[PDB]
Image (cartoon, helix red, strand yellow):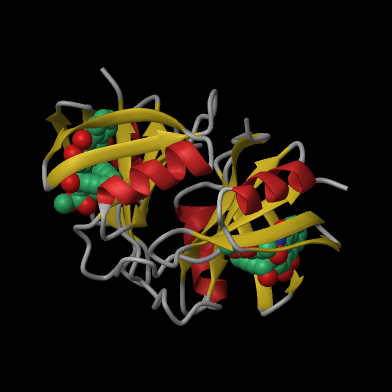
Length: 121
Length: 121
Ligand SMILES: COC(=O)/C=C(\C)[C@@]12O[C@]13c1cc(O)c4c(c1N[C@H]2C#C/C=C\C#C[C@H]3O)C(=O)c1ccccc1C4=O
Ligand SMILES: COC(=O)/C=C(\C)[C@@]12O[C@]13c1cc(O)c4c(c1N[C@H]2C#C/C=C\C#C[C@H]3O)C(=O)c1ccccc1C4=O
């Protein structure tokens, strides 16, 4: 068996990092983990409070254009209240809808990356 | 404040899903969580054993061409041993090498998605 424990982090392609920081931290409610120099420029890292896996808001992978990400799903304990909060903050939300795999909604970040919310049935 | 607890899963763009399944499960040693019909085709879902955030090996999303993913970092308790295992199993590994954020290595999946390994200091 391998010694891998979990995904430490993955990357979300953004164009404007200040606008992405403000979206993920203020609108979506993530903690800011880091905002500091990195190897290809500004390293901006965010995550839900307490979570093992974080997100890096980067602009330096040509194969990942800003806004190209899909199929990112966030677990929430209250999808209905989260959707209402997003809507109050000016975000267009699709759903929530009951699905076979939980009650789910979708929304986009400022670049067009698509983010899902899922609350178990 | 938002009720989001963690990232449930994110998507990794692959072409041949059977090939991807065997690479992630047999070669990299991930647990197979699910392999069933999904909304837009075969749903194939893997994770390091016991991890909160999983990976979905999809060919659903035109904006994510197969093999385009970068900036994914897996946490491991023994990067040296994992690299030796990957090499034994017929995978090219770059590193491991010391960095400011831990001892890291990189390799690619059958489509060219780039996967990092990190053992913090
Ligand atoms: C070029 O080969 C790669 O694909 C390398 C990687 C995917 C990483 O080496 C890279 C990282 C660059 C950083 O600036 C990092 C880190 C890197 N690690 C790998 C990664 C990543 C996600 C985007 C990136 C990158 C690379 O420049 C990093 O792990 C950190 C961890 C904790 C705090 C800060 C950092 C960083 O600032
Ligand atoms: C930003 O992406 C989203 O908004 C994704 C969704 C709202 C998902 O509903 C989607 C899913 C489609 C499935 O086929 C799923 C599932 C979906 N849940 C969300 C997701 C995702 C990643 C790619 C996608 C998609 C959607 O069609 C799903 O959670 C499963 C859980 C356990 C076993 C099987 C499945 C599935 O087969």
